[PDB]
Amino acid sequence: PPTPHLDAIERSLRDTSPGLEGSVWQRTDGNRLDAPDGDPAGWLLQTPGCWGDAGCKDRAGTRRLLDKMTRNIADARHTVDISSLAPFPNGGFEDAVVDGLKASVAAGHSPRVRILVGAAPIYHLNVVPSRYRDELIGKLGAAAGKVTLNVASMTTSKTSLSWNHSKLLVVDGKTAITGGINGWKDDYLDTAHPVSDVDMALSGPAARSAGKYLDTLWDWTCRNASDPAKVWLATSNGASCMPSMEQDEAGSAPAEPTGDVPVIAVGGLGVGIKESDPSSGYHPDLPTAPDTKCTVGLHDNTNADRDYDTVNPEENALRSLIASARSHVEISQQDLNATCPPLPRYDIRTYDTLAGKLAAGVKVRIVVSDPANRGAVGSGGYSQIKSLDEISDTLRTRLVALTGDNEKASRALCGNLQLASFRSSDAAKWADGKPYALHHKLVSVDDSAFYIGSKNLYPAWLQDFGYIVESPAAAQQLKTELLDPEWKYSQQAAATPAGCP
Image (cartoon, rainbow, N blue to C red; front, side, top):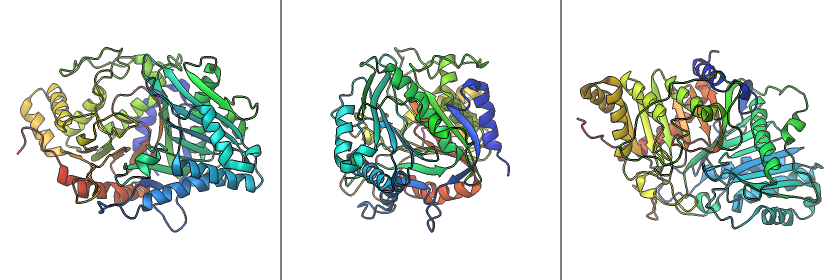
């Protein structure tokens, strides 16, 4: 069955980073979207999943998420590989890990466990790796002597603002859960104003791809533990740091197919792990478009650095996913624009690809976190814009640059764009008066191909990871479960860009 969206994306990754095929990106067949029996859309792990209700009484999404995480871990025989953005998983996120690990030990296993979080240079960790190690050992009680732990927090570049941001849970290199969800109880669980977010669950060869990606990060992390400014590392009971846990677990038993879903696994190494793919022939025309609102102080890796692309194929994967849309594109993000300075405010090539689609009559929908959510990351900050015009004005600019004339630019912008801030009910905010925070990193195209993972469309130079799936049947579920309901409530917060009918 054909895959015209994946083929275009694959063409662009082999051109961008051929040397990273098999570790930072990889196409595979034979995957399964891992739904529980009698819950066919249950691969889609949305949270809170309480559409239509400003009081959010029944969080069926959250419940399904925590359950799936517990069960995947409960099935572990050898390896459990976790990555996130610091702080370390707490609350129910942490209980899911501890309970799943106790179940695994009770079935007679001795699992190896790696937990990796990235930390911003400015971010003071309350619970450091050794304390988090000891906490887990304590909750594990007697199970503990059977579990080998590597726990690490890491920053790859203080100067270039790079650290881990991927959110992965890989068990035995065969199941994988990823998406936008950090394991932060106050934002997601214990609150009357829960963050809305989505992960997906999968099994199959694409989970081994995720393991390879985590191995790459752990190779760097184990080596750089000689620099405590970069890596804090705690292991259990004399255990070595385990750079290649996933490779060691895969041995060579070519991954078994579990279904019929084709997938591209695609991540990025941010700054400070590898400078380029020396193997790569990539040589793009970079755009040249100053921003009127903001002039960046830092060297701009998003807009103006060839080598950065070659070690961050996810950037091109996303640009060319959007470029492959023939009919419509839906984007659901925290932000399309970044805080400038220190970062560039937007990705020029992404805005151009969008402008190009607008011009060609492709329907584009952008839904972002409500600007009311502006604030510090990790402390309720879920917006980086003051107004939605910051998105529609940039698009106008690029449309004008692209079409030459300001009238055509207006046809395309007013006829083909839906732009709105997110809501999940008829209320404008949560029943407790807090605005809806959106943390999706989702892009869907033509009701066939979609991306879920941890990579934001706004400029950021982090280690990230995600999956692009091509399957009409899956897209249809995504449409029904998430995108249609999102639009039903968010259309009431639709923006009319300046200059439109």
